[PDB]
Image (cartoon, rainbow, N blue to C red; front, side):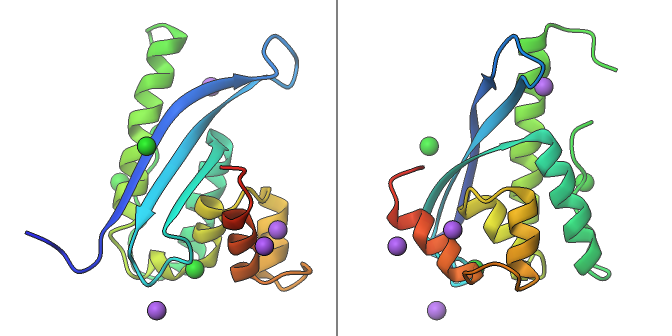
Length: 148
Ligand SMILES: [Cl-]
Ligand SMILES: [Cl-]
Ligand SMILES: [Cl-]
Ligand code: NA
Ligand code: NA
Ligand code: NA
Ligand code: NA
């Protein structure tokens, strides 16, 4: 009934950023609560857009060996709100599956995606050792800030 380690994830609250402009896009709130020793922060709240998930999947596959990486949601014939809701569902399912794998949970790019608001280029730099702070400090600083 009660597992030793639980990781709960929710993708929620899609929002249009820069609405009406060239740089308009939808992002998604990602909430996480866990007691997993793989994680630095017990709770986190970040926002990520679809192209960032696309990046994340590719990166996970790079390091995953033979552990299969879950597929993302991808024509669509409904309204934009209906498309966004289907996508939101698919992103939630993607992350649930990813979080079942001890191998995928060992990837620091995942942790910075979920528990920091570093940009993709920042995450890449951080895990390549080119940033001024460690993966842990990026995640702790975000936690201790009130940004989520
Ligand atoms: Cl929530
Ligand atoms: Cl971590
Ligand atoms: Cl899949
Ligand atoms: Na969109
Ligand atoms: Na520990
Ligand atoms: Na930081
Ligand atoms: Na701090």
